[PDB]
Amino acid sequence: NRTLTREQVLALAEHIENAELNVHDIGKVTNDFPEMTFADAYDVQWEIRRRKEARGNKIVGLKMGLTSWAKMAQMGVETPIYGFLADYFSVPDGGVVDCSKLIHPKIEAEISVVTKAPLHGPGCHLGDVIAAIDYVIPTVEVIDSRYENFKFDPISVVADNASSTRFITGGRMASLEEVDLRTLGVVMEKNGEVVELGAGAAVLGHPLSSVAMLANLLAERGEHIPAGTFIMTGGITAAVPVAPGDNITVRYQGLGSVSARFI
Ligand SMILES: [Cl-]
Ligand SMILES: [Cl-]
Figure 1 (spheres, rainbow, N blue to C red):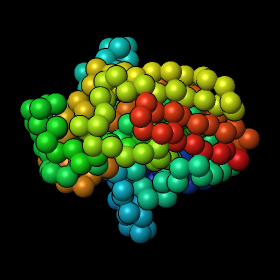
Figure 2: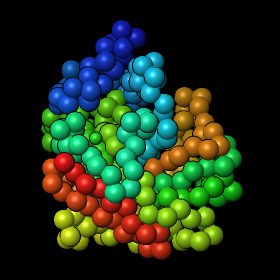
Figure 3: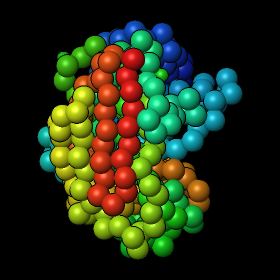
């Protein structure tokens, strides 16, 4: 279920990462390698991860995209996708994001979890995930597809590490007992104006299901979710463009707010 040569995987990884590192958008890689499979795309993504680790980056978490059944159906995919988060992606709550290091960023409001017990697939589901959750933490992702392309292409997006680039944790942490994730309301404000609303249920119907799907996805490559893993479970809100000068604040029901300043 792979069509790329290893040489092509390595080259695509270098090419795609270079788009991020040099803040230069590129054509979607499936235009040049149309046979690419998801396995190919993850090969590329994990090779990007290796390149980052090899230069000393710590990988500090994972993120989930396509966490909408409607969107999945639209894309003709049966599962979400994931990407990894590098240490330098992290931005503190209220902190600065330098848009000059980004291409055409957008933000999505999410709820993240930190696990306290290992999880694995295949066949992982919500019930398995519950006992493994340490706490939840409001998180805003800055996503920034390295592609010039207007239309979403899941395989190219996976290869591009699911468009990951920054994440801002903030608000207040909470145990599962303290929060109802499905009805957890989120209000995204940009420059003082409410721009998106949504609830945690927008992630698959239940944000913790994302963790289970992640575990099953990882199991496809013989990996799992170690205890202590930070996972951004998926965009609750539609993604919102951000540009220099923008200030955002995302309020989470009972969990305070996450803010960032874009310069
Ligand atoms: Cl930055
Ligand atoms: Cl296009």
